[PDB]
Amino acid sequence: VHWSAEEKQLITGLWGKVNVAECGAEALARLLIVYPWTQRFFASFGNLSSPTAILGNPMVRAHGKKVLTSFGDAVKNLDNIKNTFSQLSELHCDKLHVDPENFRLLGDILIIVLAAHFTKDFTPECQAAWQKLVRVVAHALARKYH
Amino acid sequence: VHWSAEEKQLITGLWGKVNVAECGAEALARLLIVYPWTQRFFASFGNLSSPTAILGNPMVRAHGKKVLTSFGDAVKNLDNIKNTFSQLSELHCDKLHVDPENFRLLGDILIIVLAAHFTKDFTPECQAAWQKLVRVVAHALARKYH
Amino acid sequence: VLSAADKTNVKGIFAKIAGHAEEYGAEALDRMFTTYPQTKTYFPHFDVSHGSAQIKGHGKKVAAALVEAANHIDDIAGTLSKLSDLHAQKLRVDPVNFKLLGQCFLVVVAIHHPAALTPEVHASLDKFLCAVGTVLTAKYR
Amino acid sequence: VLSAADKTNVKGIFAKIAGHAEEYGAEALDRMFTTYPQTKTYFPHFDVSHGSAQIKGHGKKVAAALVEAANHIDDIAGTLSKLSDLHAQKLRVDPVNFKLLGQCFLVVVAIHHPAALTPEVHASLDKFLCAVGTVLTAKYR
Ligand code: HEM
Ligand code: HEM
Ligand code: HEM
Ligand code: HEM
């Protein structure tokens, strides 16, 4: 996959301003509130019943961060994501058999979350870099399939 | 991906008894019918005003013919599909620009066809090599993307 | 939605089904298994092998409900407004999977009736087979 | 498909978005080309450059009917079918882009009302967008 010197800035630049804590809680909380199907996989966490509770429960408010922080690992190397999420791609496919369209449903949820914490500080041309990222992510985690 | 002793046989053997003109013909046609949006894709095929004008549009069946024959070049290339479709992925991806959701669609309609022409000759255990088959083909048709 | 003409292709195929409910379903499901085995995990409490009394059992409902649903095609989300609550909330099913049954459910009809599933009548079913899938995943939409 | 809690959430976000449709629609659209250059094929006699005349005169209508659909929701499926042709029959849009516009429309809202588009309101719209999603692709299902 191709990346550039301008997409490297929109990405590496904005990464170092993400309050991972909250947005990783925000977007896992949303996934769980947005597509309610997405709740089955997270049975082990407890109370996910009322949309507002979903955020109050602090396993998501914890496990959420591990998603965004996850995305951390990538940013260090846009040029070996393949080998990065690969060990991680075994974890979502073999063990907890997760349908990758959902790898599109948090990527899309997680761009929306940046979207509300960076206002016009979130460039049309930016967002794009950030899809390409969580698009490249999405399908890395789906290496251990076809 | 792994093909085995019980997998090679049903692919190779069923392949050798498919009327590639008919099966290809009813293939492209269901897609042309069942999902009316792809017709723009084949706008330079002419009269595509009605299910019956569609089935008989000679060039429809002069297309289905070249699509099921393709698969056949893969039928012989199991462990080698990626290289096989190389250029033909650059056709759909970079050129034509078909949303990979359609590889599956024209995929799942093919399957549908094996059941029509072959009825009981289409075992559960057969179906699945005509699944995986079609999935893997679809996956290379998506190689010049991510 | 589904319109005057859809309302007769679909009504079409289920009439031609109708008497072999229990098979087509059981059979749709086996194919729902040996083709997409990552569907299995909703049935770890169930005998998933070709033609046990279980896929037979569970099969006739899957077929029965779908029929009861064309009998009153005019309201699929209230005739099945008992079955949506279940699926969408406790088993919680990924829609990805309704598209694995559906298609798998078509692939059955084909084997048993290739001249009833004419591409025009094929069209309306996948249609029907969306809306049922929708209805039953309604606790999301 | 769209109950009471939804109706209230959906109506809400709207009279919020309302009096800035001539730029909430242009933005959205200005974002679906710049993240998604493939949707550009539907626009080859369009001025695609940043801030141009044809996009803002357009985008205006993408909400102009996005909110006419909002303030008449009891029947989205009817008020929008007019276009459900222009979309389903005339231009024929791949349904996999109602999304790519579904979203780039929630990258706008988000930017300008990040404290209104709570998850639940985010849900209703994204399900109302799944409403204006299906109706506009009527000709297939
Ligand atoms: C945006 C793409 C995603 C990324 C990058 C990601 C990343 C991660 C990470 C970093 C872990 C940490 C494991 C640990 O702490 O031991 C994890 C585990 C897990 N993931 Fe994901 N994830 C994504 C999407 C999803 C989706 C859609 C689901 C399913 C709804 C999912 C389901 C899970 C589950 C159920 C666990 C572990 C549960 C447990 O600890 O018992 N992930 N993932
Ligand atoms: C399912 C796997 C597919 C395979 C193996 C395949 C194969 C091919 C081949 C071999 C050609 C033309 C090569 C030649 O004679 O020069 C072609 C052309 C074309 N294909 Fe596909 N295809 C697939 C899926 C699709 C889908 C899903 C669509 C549309 C939704 C599509 C749309 C087209 C179009 C519009 C052309 C151009 C025809 C022309 O200019 O002559 N293909 N495809
Ligand atoms: C047209 C779509 C479907 C129909 C008509 C259907 C039919 C039914 C019916 C009638 C029941 C409950 C009967 C009763 O308890 O009295 C049921 C439950 C169930 N459904 Fe479905 N189903 C459909 C889709 C799916 C799919 C695709 C899956 C796979 C994930 C699924 C998984 C289940 C499971 C695991 C149960 C629990 C049954 C048990 O454990 O006894 N359903 N279904
Ligand atoms: C929220 C769903 C959508 C709405 C409300 C919408 C709205 C509109 C409206 C109001 C028009 C002008 C028609 C008239 O005045 O008769 C139009 C035209 C058009 N639309 Fe959409 N649209 C939607 C989705 C899409 C998407 C995703 C695409 C691209 C893939 C698209 C492609 C087009 C095209 C190519 C035209 C032709 C107008 C021209 O040549 O300037 N529409 N749309």
Image (spheres, coloured by chain):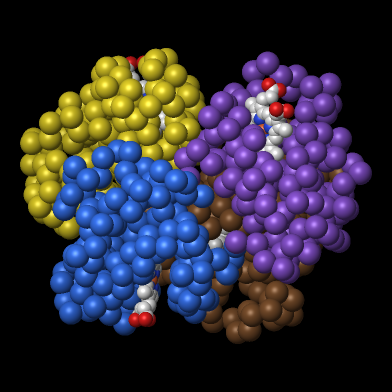
Chain colours: A brown, B yellow, C blue, D purple
**Viewer-nearest residue: D19 or D26:** D19
Q: Residue B69 in the image: state x and y as whole percent.
A: 21, 27
Q: Residue D108 in the image: state x and y as whole percent.
A: 79, 45
Residue D107 is left or right of residue B131, and the answer is right
> Does residue C75 sit above or below C10 in this rendering?
below
- Residue situated furthest bottom in the rendering: A46
> Does residue D70 sit above or below B143 in this rendering?
below
Residue D17 is left or right of residue A105, and the answer is right
> Does residue B32 sit above or below A28 in this rendering?
above
Q: Residue C49 in the image: state x and y as whole percent.
A: 18, 72
Name the image quarter holding residue D44: top right
**Viewer-nearest residue: B142 or B104:** B104
At 65% from the left and 23% from the top, the residue drawn is D43
At 47% from the left and 63% from the top, the residue drawn is C76
> Does residue B74 sit above or below A144 in this rendering?
above
At 72% from the left and 54% from the top, the residue drawn is D73
For ligand 2, give the image quadrant.
Answer: top left
Q: Would residue D8 be seen by someone viewing this image from the given angle?
A: yes
Q: Residue D135 in the image: state x and y as whole percent.
A: 59, 45
Residue D119 is left or right of residue C89, and the answer is right
